[PDB]
Amino acid sequence: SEKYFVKNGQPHFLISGEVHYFRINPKLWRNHLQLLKQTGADTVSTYIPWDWHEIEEDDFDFEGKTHPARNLIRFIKLCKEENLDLIVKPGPYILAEYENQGLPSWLLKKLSKNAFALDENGNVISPDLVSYLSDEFLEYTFKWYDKVMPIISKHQKEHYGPITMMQLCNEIGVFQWLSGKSDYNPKVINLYKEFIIQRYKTIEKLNSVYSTNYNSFDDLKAPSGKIKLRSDYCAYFDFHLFFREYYNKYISILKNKIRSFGINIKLTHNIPGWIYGNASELPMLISTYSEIMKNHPDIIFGLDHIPEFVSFRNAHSDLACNKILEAMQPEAPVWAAEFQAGTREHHVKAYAKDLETFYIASLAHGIKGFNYYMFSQGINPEGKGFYGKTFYFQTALDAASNKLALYDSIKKVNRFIRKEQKDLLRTNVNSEICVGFYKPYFFTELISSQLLKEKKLNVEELGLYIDPRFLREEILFNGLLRGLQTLNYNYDVVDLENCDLKSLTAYKQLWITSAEFMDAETQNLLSEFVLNGGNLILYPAVPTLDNYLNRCEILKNNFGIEFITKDSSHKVSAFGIEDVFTAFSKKQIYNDTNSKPIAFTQENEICGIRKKIGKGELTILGFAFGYTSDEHLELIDKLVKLNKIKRELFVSDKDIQFVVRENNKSRYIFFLNYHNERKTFNYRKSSKSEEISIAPFSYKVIKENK
Amino acid sequence: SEKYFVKNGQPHFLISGEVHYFRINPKLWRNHLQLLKQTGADTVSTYIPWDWHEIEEDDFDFEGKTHPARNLIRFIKLCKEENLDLIVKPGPYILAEYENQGLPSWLLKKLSKNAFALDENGNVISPDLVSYLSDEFLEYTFKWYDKVMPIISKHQKEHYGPITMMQLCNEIGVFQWLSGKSDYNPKVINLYKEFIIQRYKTIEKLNSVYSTNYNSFDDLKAPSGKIKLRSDYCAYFDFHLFFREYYNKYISILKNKIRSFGINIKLTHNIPGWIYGNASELPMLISTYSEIMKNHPDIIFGLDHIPEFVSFRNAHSDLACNKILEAMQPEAPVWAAEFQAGTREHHVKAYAKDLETFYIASLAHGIKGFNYYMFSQGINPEGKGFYGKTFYFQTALDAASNKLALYDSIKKVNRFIRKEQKDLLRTNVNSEICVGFYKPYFFTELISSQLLKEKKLNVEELGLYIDPRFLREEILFNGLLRGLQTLNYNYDVVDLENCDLKSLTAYKQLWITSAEFMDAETQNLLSEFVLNGGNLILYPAVPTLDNYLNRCEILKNNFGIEFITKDSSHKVSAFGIEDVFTAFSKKQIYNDTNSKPIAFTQENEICGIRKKIGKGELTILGFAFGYTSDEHLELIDKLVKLNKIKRELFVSDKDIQFVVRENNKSRYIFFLNYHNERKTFNYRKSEEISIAPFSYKVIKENK
Ligand SMILES: O=[N+]([O-])c1ccc(O[C@H]2O[C@H](CO)[C@@H](O)[C@H](O)[C@H]2O)cc1
Ligand SMILES: O=[N+]([O-])c1ccc(O[C@H]2O[C@H](CO)[C@@H](O)[C@H](O)[C@H]2O)cc1
Ligand SMILES: [Ca+2]
């Protein structure tokens, strides 16, 4: 029961390459398509830029009347002739390093100030950055759809055209995220006031939750400036809930408009979050799509992977992101809408030898399809390049359609996929560990992020000490998930929201990284999990508040935990590992009632315990560790071993990463060497040992029959 | 010509390894020192931790009475017996991931409130962090010196002992940097007031500079919070100057105390600033030692180089840092007091094959000595590690003196260095390009840094648009310097403060990355440079203000420049290069009378001019570009070619970096491959070689 794309009721690996017709000499379009097809790619992908085709207000060219490379119709016809399916992405935003992110110059000059995203002061955040639900913006977006959408509709697969998929806009919220500011446009404010009225019904109900003293809803303003009171936190938390409804309204409006043209193809969206070759903030961005993914089973989200290099420094980002996408979208294949090929920036090199390993590591890490971005380099015509004339470097093909070094790497990877896809797409890893994804810890893009200008969340001011962003980046993303991957223990991630208990009972262990706050439903779910026979590992805190920081002690009471928070040395001992460095002086100190103490402070106070509760097991650690020392890996390994979980292989070099994927028929062993060392090692199945030599930053794949 | 260490009257490449006796099994001390010597290393370096030897107040153990690893006397004997010189570093601060950063637990327990660094509300910043000039802190510091300095004096090189250098404290100011927090201890603020009174003499003089409305110096409060007004910018600027004098005062008290024991060896200090494997902030940290470097020509500053990996992503960091240290310390060798060996962080790998390439690149980039940090791993004794049990990973030796992969890399690099040091140390690059270092742009560690979470400096609130940190990081460090190195053009850096005109006239071009403000002295210096025959390249602004943001247009008026600041598309054309991405909407649009327009906005407005002024040449670009496109390399290459500057070689692969080092007799060509690609290329003077990924090749030529 893997999820994978299907062609004529067979497992099909979606292999696309991105080829920007608008940035290639049209005399060479066919050569680019033939060379893509010759790699074993089945699909080609492109933006259709609004700025490129609405050359002036109400002057459209899709036929190359005014510039040969405006002949979208001819590009579509060539894709059909060269037996490639086509993904089209008509925006309105395309990003794509295109002037004004794809929006017409004439549009941005004409729009009045209230079409734009505005800061708390009423000023324009950026001259390219519109307010998504601006009446003016959506009027012009609709007139752009009125011209491009009939073309897309006529050329759909169901009309024997090549068009199989369409992206709606591009990375909703990404422009906002990188700007470092949130949108306070008066459309946003007014929609937020309606959301608050709908949510609370009476000002008394809102006052009771927030601990505010408003006389009426007319006194409540959209939250701005720093969080100083728990009532400011509550307002911001609802502001985050609102923005998820807001992005759902945007994509809904676009989708309803598109469907009205007879467009029945698969609709997509693309997830931003990588920056400087890490993706620790991506889970924050995917979390902004929570309401889209609940309301639209028919929009498939795909990842925009930009690793830039392939090493232990970022080995864990693609797997964690693939796992988190699966957690939020479990009924669709994990795929990369944008799968790095070459480099968007001259000064940031993309080596074929890095990317080839990333491609193989992505297959190890469960990817089921991808679109090489950029397969073909572009040259911007007519000064449309945001940052210079050349679009991408170190691609598979240069703009002229010459093969570059990466072409042979992609041909190699694609050849393996086409030979193995029928088995490989149907393989799973044996995950005996589940890691809880608690989305509200990620709902901070308005107040706390790697990219927000203003740090608005200081939890110490609220009488708290566990910052949710610190927890989800350093304890979970760069900590637990990194540690498990480094130790070669398979894990799955499961979204705790509306989570079915039956979807947790298959695991030997459930791991919850918890702050001091957690909603009643999740506290009850984890309670029922243990009582019914589940094995829970919970740290660094038993929560005692709900998402509004009001009292909620359900899980503490159901587990018979008593604790006091006390200051000590950062270093604790745990399971007989000395000098385990922990993130906080404050730790939870548990009494040893009906429990085994397994962790101790420098004053020998109990900061961790194990107990049996109903049919289940609980391990609580009152301290925070990620992976910033060897003791942290020793501690994770010890915790996993509490339930006799074993690695799939014995490998003589602990720095070698492996993944075993198998079904009934076949076993694939992926070895990954994320280190600048030629490694010679031996291995065997945990049930004579084979010797292997692996180059720096390289891979081996072994296939076994049975 | 060149500055280098000397041994037996000959050029000597200082090869030191860091070995923390206090973190090593004393039964294996001799074994560590023998394995270090066997790599060809000549020196061993260590902290002498105050907490480790003053075990209780006025109870000193330097002879292993209470713990065998407290036997400093025996470690010194072993260095002598195994023929290694010794660098000692007795603090008071040692940092070194040692609990309390090396200060005794008993001291920190007992010190009054007024001995600690205080926030602007009078609260202790950190139970770890004393005020450097606390009378109570210096009293106890001095009682520690009274016991450890006689031991160092005994064994110092001027008494023919093994101790050749001593470090004073450790990374002075590093805590103000990483925290963003200034010390507001009333003792520090009293010193700040004295500094201001001494500087301005009367409140009237200060009011005329700051545009303040004080009736006396009694109305004057230390700056704090966000800069909202130009008067706040002025106060914070002098607060930065004050902290450079404050650090000078601290190091001077330590130095005078040390000299009183008759310790006459070379004193040192160490420069922090690398994080996450780049060093774009280190020039800010070096700027904090400006007053020390001016007043103490007998204190050698060395660099703390922490590259973490070796690729095109960080290739430019170590050269830029080495060049800026040479600019501020021209009479002493450029050396790394802490030269990455292994990793402080288990999860941040240090590959022997990366570090080997970094060591050879350091030689190409002009390093004259270094101290492998950490040569030997350590095990923290009885809880005294701030982090876990282990100190460093992937070192040359583990804590039990096991050889690890890096050992063989250090032995190979050391053998090369010993074979070549007599000629290599006496080689320089031929730099025809000089890049100006304007230190006031770097004086922002209290208000604007990569480490400072929230920014106190927002120049738009002051009617400016060129932020000095954005300029010195993106336009200068990751822009011009990265670009010249990528293009294989030699540059030197020169400190513009008190700068000799004579020392600019050797160069065919001087490059100035200018904000809207620049002091009268530097404006006068650059005026005289061009008028006397110099070729100046200046962008992205003709300055119009001084360091206090008061009108100063000396350079503008001397050069006959007129401009209006106007908004346009980020892209300009320059020297016929289309689509040059520039940082700002706002650009300087120049009157072109007596001038050649060479750059244009999307609307064809003149945003760059060339001009003859007296006997020299001026190139002004009213726009900011770094290195974020191939057009940026094209533009730097075009600008360098205006004065017919040539690379020292033609190399067939543009992605191969090279450094040609020569003297009259000897040439070394260092080829560096910072890319994950096997490269085959050929070279000739302005012959076909293969280099592995992240690797190197050195070629010698007799002249
Ligand atoms: O300039 N801009 O407004 C702008 C620039 C870049 C941008 O996104 C791009 O860079 C992000 C950071 O690396 C990626 O996470 C994202 O996937 C990618 O598409 C969006 C807007
Ligand atoms: O926690 N602390 O108080 C603390 C931590 C680290 C520290 O300095 C160390 O790390 C810096 C940042 O990477 C380096 O630039 C510097 O060279 C090195 O010595 C100083 C104090
Ligand atoms: Ca003039």
Image (cartoon, coloured by chain):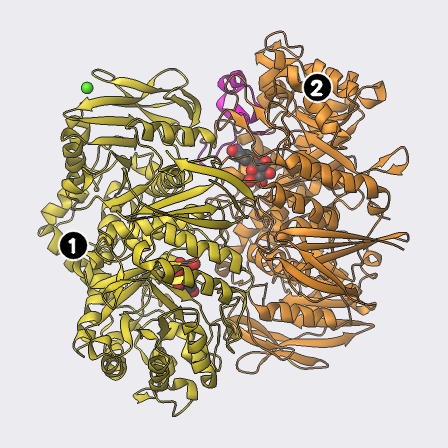
Chain colours: A orange, B yellow
Residue A229 at x, y = what percent? 50, 55
Magenta span covers which residues?
A95-122
Q: Which residue is mark 1?
A: B196
Tell me the subunit letter for badge 1: B
Quarter of image, res A499: bottom right
The residue depicted at 47 percent of the width and 57 percent of the height is B356
State left or right for residue B610 relative to residue A624.
left
Mark 2 or 1: in front is: 2
Residue B552 at x, y = what percent? 17, 34
Question: Which dot marks residue B495?
Answer: none
Residue B45 at x, y = what percent? 36, 72
Q: Classify 10 Å Cα crowding around label 1: few (below 14), some (14-19), many (20 and above).
A: many
| Residue A96 lies in the magenta stretch | yes
Tell me the subunit letter for badge 2: A
The residue depicted at 75 percent of the width and 32 percent of the height is A41
Q: Is residue A181 visible?
A: no
State left or right for residue A139 relative to residue B158.
right
SS of the residue at dot 1?
helix
Q: Ligand 1, what quadrant?
A: top right
Q: Is residue A223 above or below residue B131?
A: above
Label 2 sits on what residue type?
Arg
Alpha-carbon span between mark 2 and mark 1: 73 Å
Tell which residue pokes out farthest to the front in this image.
B702
Label 1 sits on what residue type?
Ile
Q: Is residue A586 visible?
A: yes
Tell which residue pokes out farthest to the bottom in this image.
B65
Q: Between B128 and B672, which is closer to the camera in this rendering?
A: B672
